[PDB]
Amino acid sequence: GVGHLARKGTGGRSSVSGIVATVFGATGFLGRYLVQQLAKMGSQVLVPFRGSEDSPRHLKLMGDLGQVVPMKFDPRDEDSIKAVMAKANVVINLIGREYETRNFSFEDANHHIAEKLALVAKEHGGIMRYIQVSCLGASVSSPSRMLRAKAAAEEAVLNALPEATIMRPATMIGTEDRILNPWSMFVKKYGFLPLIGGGTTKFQPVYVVDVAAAIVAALKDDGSSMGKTYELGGPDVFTTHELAEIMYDMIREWPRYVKLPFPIAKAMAAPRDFMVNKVPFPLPSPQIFNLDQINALTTDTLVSDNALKFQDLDLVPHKLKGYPVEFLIQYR
Amino acid sequence: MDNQFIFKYSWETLPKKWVKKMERSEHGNRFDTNTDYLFQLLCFLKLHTYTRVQVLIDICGVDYPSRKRRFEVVYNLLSTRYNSRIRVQTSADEVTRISSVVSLFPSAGWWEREVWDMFGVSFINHPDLRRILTDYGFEGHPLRKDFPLSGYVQVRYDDPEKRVVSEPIEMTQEFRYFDFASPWE
Amino acid sequence: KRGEIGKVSGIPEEHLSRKVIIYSPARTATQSGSGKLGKWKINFVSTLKWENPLMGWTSTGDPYANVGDSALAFDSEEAAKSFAERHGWDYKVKKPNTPLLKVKSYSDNFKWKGNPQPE
Amino acid sequence: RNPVGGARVHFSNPEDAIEVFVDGYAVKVPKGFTVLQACEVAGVDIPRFCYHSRLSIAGNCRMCLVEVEKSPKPVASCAMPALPGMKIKTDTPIAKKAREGVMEFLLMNHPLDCPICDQGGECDLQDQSMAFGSDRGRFTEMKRSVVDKNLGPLVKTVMTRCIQCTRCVRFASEVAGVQDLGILGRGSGEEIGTYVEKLMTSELSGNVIDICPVGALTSKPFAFKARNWELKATETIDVSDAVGSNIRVDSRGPEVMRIIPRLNEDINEEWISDKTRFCYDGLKRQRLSDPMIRDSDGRFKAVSWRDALAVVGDIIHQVKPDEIVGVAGQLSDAESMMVLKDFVNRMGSDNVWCEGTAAGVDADLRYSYLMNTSISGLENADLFLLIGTQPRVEAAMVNARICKTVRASNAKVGYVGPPAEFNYDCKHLGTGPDTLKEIAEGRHPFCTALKNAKNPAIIVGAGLFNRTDKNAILSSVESIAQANNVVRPDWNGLNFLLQYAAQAAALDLGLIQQSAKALESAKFVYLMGADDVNVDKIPKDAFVVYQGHHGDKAVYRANVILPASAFTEKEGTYENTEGFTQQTVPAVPTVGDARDDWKIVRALSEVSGVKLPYNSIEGVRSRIKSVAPNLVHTDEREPAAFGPSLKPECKEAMSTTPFQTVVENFYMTNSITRASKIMAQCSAVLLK
Amino acid sequence: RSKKSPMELISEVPPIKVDGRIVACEGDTNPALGHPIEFICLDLNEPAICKYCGLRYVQDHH
Amino acid sequence: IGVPPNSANLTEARRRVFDFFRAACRSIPTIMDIYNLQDVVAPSQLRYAISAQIRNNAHITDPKVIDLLIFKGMEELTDIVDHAKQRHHIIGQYVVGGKTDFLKNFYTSNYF
Ligand SMILES: NC(=O)C1=CN([C@@H]2O[C@H](COP(=O)(O)OP(=O)(O)OC[C@H]3O[C@@H](n4cnc5c(N)ncnc54)[C@H](OP(=O)(O)O)[C@@H]3O)[C@@H](O)[C@H]2O)C=CC1
Ligand SMILES: CCCCCCCCCCCC(=O)SCCNC(=O)CCNC(=O)[C@H](O)C(C)(C)COP(=O)(O)O
Ligand code: SF4
Ligand code: SF4
Ligand code: FES
Ligand SMILES: [Zn+2]
């Protein structure tokens, strides 16, 4: 699958790599880093967005001039997706949602959109590399509804395009993550950090920059990545307790844990589940008490011992104890 | 008072071992002296009754890469009492420390700091000799002839790093040098 | 090479190990004037340029892209050699090619061919 | 003070040296110099329009008028001989008033088209008008005009800007040797032209663009492309032929705009050929830029460097050591040839050679493949014997200097070879080997002139080396050289003229073919830019690797394509026909993912499990120093050491087949010109 | 008529008839608002083109 | 205070080098507080960094060049003592840190 890169510079901002990528859902957490690392090599990035035109505003700084071109699109409409995908030798999918909106359910936002993006790339032959980003715990048997949709999108993408790599990272940590920041916000607002499982479940936090660099390396491979499913995980197997301890270490506050068994937190997150319908379609999104996340935090999520990892791409993840979590000094 | 009078007076009154080059013209009466006699000459020219030069207009450096003593330091002086201007020049290379005149002229401090920033010439007994114009942590002296016009580093905002960062320079359109020199000059 | 001035100058270490050519540019073939001669220049061999894929402009990432042509000029070979020696640049010197004044006279246009030889 | 432009005055004797006062300064000049030359020695540069140091004197423009004490009227310094005790004055009011008079006359019928003139920022007329001219024009009447005429696909002609200096006519009559241009008419209506509709067919015809001081004669391919101030000038050399002319490559960014000559009194002498001048067009067409390997169906897919090197290194280990053949190209530099020779030698093979003269030539003594008489030394010869060579198409500058010697010293030229066209008078002695036997035995009328010549010059061609009777011919030539004295301690006359830029370096480095039937019994052929070889000889089972910068017939048969950089993109050493080593300077960046030849060969060595001690360009030159130590001592005039006496006696028999022509199309010789667009319209209308 | 390039537009203007052997082209009715004066020799059969304007001039009678 | 007069021998240059090194070492506690370097770097790794810079600049034998180097180092130290430079700058300069080199460079680009 060689032919998707042609270096025409010094590998700087004004250099020219022969990559023209369309990054769907780049206005979120991972997109802000993936687009930045794509633009640094001189790759033109098309950023399709929906809604307000201020959402992709921060991505214009990453390219030199015209390297980043935001374009409006509608997931429901199909000709818009084809229009925003025409000039693209690479397509990267980052579209996904962890809570449920009445406009877009768990299956719609995680599976159907991925199906449409894979199909449109199929008819529009010419995308040399296609990347779809699921979640590490993606499995059909997973109690969480989001993970099952991501898994189904995995088989859908692999069936619609056997050359599509599926990078499958774990919980991300960064300046704008949705795990460490809500914890600090809750601590500064209520004084205690609730534990939906008593700080027992084990998971593998990964730095978002490491995941973006992994996607970049998968793009700039020797052709081994094609039709593979990497499992991007951090170096240390933390837990909900030890990560909260690091967060208290950074935020500089005396620890105060309120243990909460799974049933009580499940019933406390239940009200939003059956109140998605109301006079307004929008409703305040969950912060730490997402029912889907609580169900996902019942089975330990670790990188498979017999699956591809960071070291199979010649990358070493950052140790999530110093620089990765230095953003927490803003609450200090 | 005049270039014809100042030249003849300074020829006689000044010690001969100080000045080694005296041009008298309409562009300006210049005195070229060794760097170890600059302070002595400028103190004499600030206190003598008939050469009351009490204003230091500016201190500039000139870069001559073809000379052994690369840098030329020029002291433009003004005498308000006699309505005359005197220019005093010295020469120094990149690793010689010339004497500072802040003791005589308090205004010499910022000009000497600018000369050190722009050319790399250090001044002995200067109360504080630090860069005054270039950015903090600037490496290199821009006003040298061997320093590239656009420099070596460039500044941009790094969103993942959440700060303004410095990167090696990479121009989208390079500076086009046009050679207009004529062979019949 | 005693590149001490290069170390106390501010040039980054990467650009202090460049290989330069000290040469005297020659007279252009389209003009007969000899005014732009006798000056020596340092050629940094800066060729890494490409094309901007937005407007076709010439982009570069080399600071010494035009210094030796715009500002850095010397009056003799010794001055340029000393400059390169103090800045720690590996240099090679190209001696200029100079014309040789031969004897030319207007009467040579009109020269006897010789007695008609029936050879 | 120093002479203008660092001009070197050669005093034959101290006795014959008159004294003149250019501006009150004592100046010593030989008897024979003119007032202009004496002023040039004294640092004063006189204005000139019609005077050229390589052309005959013709005092037309009257711009170099100076004041002489014992003269009632100003004298033309270009033509006035210098006399002892003469006091010249250049900066007097008389000389000035003369100069602003002449400039006013010259700028009277000149068209007001500086902005559209291609000589805009490089015109002698306006540069001298600013300096030595006046400020205001007194002319208001109607100007004259002339129609423009077609002189071919190379010279664009706008004759309204002609100042009638007749430098083009003098060049065509004296240097080019093709009298087709002249001054037609009388008075202000006189015009430069061919009268009849004909095109400039001389190989040195493009040099009229430079000698023209105005924009009357300009390059047609380089029309309106750019101005001179936009161009970066790189002083590089030629690789088109084995002369190695000094050129000056002008570029605007990553592409080359034009090539103009550069002064070298010993090689080209201010002139370059039409193949040199307009070869820059092919450097941007059909350029290989990506590694490519054939597919099962038979198409080239673009592949990365790592995989192509892996494929070639995997296939190189499956062939027998004597099955490996490496062929260098004509544009190859010495470092890449040394790297290729080392690589092939370590693999167990000894079949390394160059495109052209590589049939088994003995490069054992270095006088047998070099111009043992320097090119500039050909000006002292009295008789040229061109044995089976056509310098007009092979080495155009050597032909130019031969024409100079013939028209100035009245030398005699005897030619033995196939019928051809010469720009100087030549006697057709014969057309084959039998003529050499006739010359050797004697009684031939040309032998009388040969033995009655003080400095004879025999010039054998490189084409005499692919024949089966090569040793017999080289022995007959040496017998002629010995019997009729041409090789003496005070004068060496035996010369061999090469055609390719890489032949001299290849012969110095020992790149000589061992087996004649080596490319028929091969299995891995590494064509290092060698597309001038007939690929049909290569067996169909051979794995052919083509490492070059341009696509030709060798590409259609190669299995792996490794892109390379051109001569304007790398530092390489090339050796002349006379043994003079010069270096090219990079001017433009390499296009695409192409690498230097020596880098590609060394990387292939590393991938093929063969270690090469050197890893940089300086490491290669140290290795060369142990093989041909004169290829690293660049810009040195080292003469030959031994003579033809060392060669063993070789009693072969000369064949009867007449000599052949090696160059059929002068504009289609190397791969760069073969890919150029200018050389097509030049080989379609200029060749007959 | 933006589809017509300036080349096609200047290729449609009929050549100007001039009685003499030479014509001076200034480019506009007001000399100061045109291009530098250009003297064109009408001694051929094809129309003679101004190198500034692109206007073509042809000899009228002879 | 004032810039010291230019040295006359190598012994004075060595004395100035040692004085500057001692001043920089005494400046270490201030940097660990002005910038949050407490849980970042050991108080000796930086000291080793200054020692390494002094040691790889230790082939100079010209007293004037040594004095200029000391002056530039003192200027850098004074700038770092103030809040002039950004935090990551010192962490980007002051932290201590397989087939063939030629073949990797060849795979990278033609311009070595
Ligand atoms: N901890 C984490 O963040 C983890 C993330 N992942 C996966 O990584 C991917 C991206 O990471 P992240 O950046 O955190 O995801 P974000 O939710 O932070 O960003 C979501 C992106 O998807 C777009 N999007 C969401 N729903 C829709 C929709 N219905 N139609 C169109 N666009 C939509 C958003 O656009 P808008 O903002 O305009 O809606 C936004 O650009 C997601 O798929 C996520 O599941 C995997 C494991 C853990
Ligand atoms: C955060 C702090 C900011 C500032 C940090 C410092 C930044 C600048 C670092 C200093 C830069 C320099 O090169 S300034 C110091 C450079 N000067 C020298 O190296 C003198 C030559 N060296 C020698 O003479 C000997 O090797 C010697 C090493 C003395 C010992 O060995 P001995 O005695 O056996 O002889
Ligand atoms: S030849 Fe010279 S003076 Fe005449 S138009 Fe051209 S640039 Fe102007
Ligand atoms: S065409 Fe050029 S070289 Fe020839 S006579 Fe006219 S001005 Fe002179
Ligand atoms: S140069 Fe002498 S008259 Fe023209
Ligand atoms: Zn007009």
Image: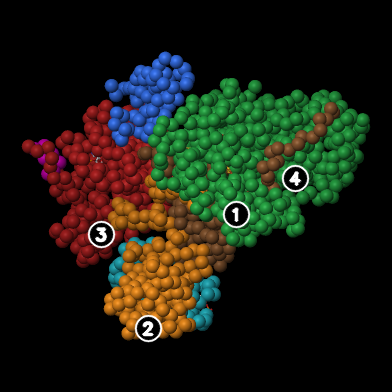
Q: Label 1 near label 4: C-beta < 8 Å? A: no
Chain under disc 1: D
Question: In the image, is residue A277 part of the stretch drawn in magenta?
Answer: yes
Q: Residue at x 64, y 47 (%)?
A: D80
Q: Which mark is residue D377?
A: 4
Magenta span: chief secondary structure: loop
Q: What residue is shown with label 1? A: D69
Q: Residues within 10 Å of mark 2 (few under 14, many from 20)?
A: some
Q: Residues within 10 Å of mark 4 (few under 14, many from 20)?
A: some
Q: Nearer the viewer, residue D210 or A117?
A: D210
Q: Colour of chain E?
A: blue
Q: Quadrant of the N terminus of chain F?
A: bottom left
Q: Nearer the viewer, residue F72 or A312?
A: F72
Position above or below: B47 against D632: below
Q: Which residue appears farthest toward the left when viewing the image?
A: A279
| Distance between the alpha carbons at the discs numbered 3 and 2 | 64 Å
Q: Which residue appears farthest toward the front when viewing the image?
A: D72
Give the chain coloured cyan: F
Residue D407 lies left or right of residue F67; in this view the side is: right
Q: Colour of chain C?
A: brown
| Distance between the alpha carbons at the discs numbered 4 and 3 | 82 Å
Camera-side mark, 2 or 1:
1
| Distance between the alpha carbons at the discs numbered 3 and 1 | 94 Å
The answer to whether tags 2 and 4 share a subunit is no
| Distance between the alpha carbons at the discs numbered 4 and 1 | 41 Å
Residue A72 percent location from the top left of the image: 24, 35
Where are the magenta residues, as a range? A271-278
Q: Colour of chain D?
A: green
Residue A212 percent location from the top left of the image: 35, 47
Q: Quadrant of residue A6?
A: top left
Indicate the amino acid at tag 4.
Gly
Q: Which residue appears farthest toward the top when viewing the image?
A: E61
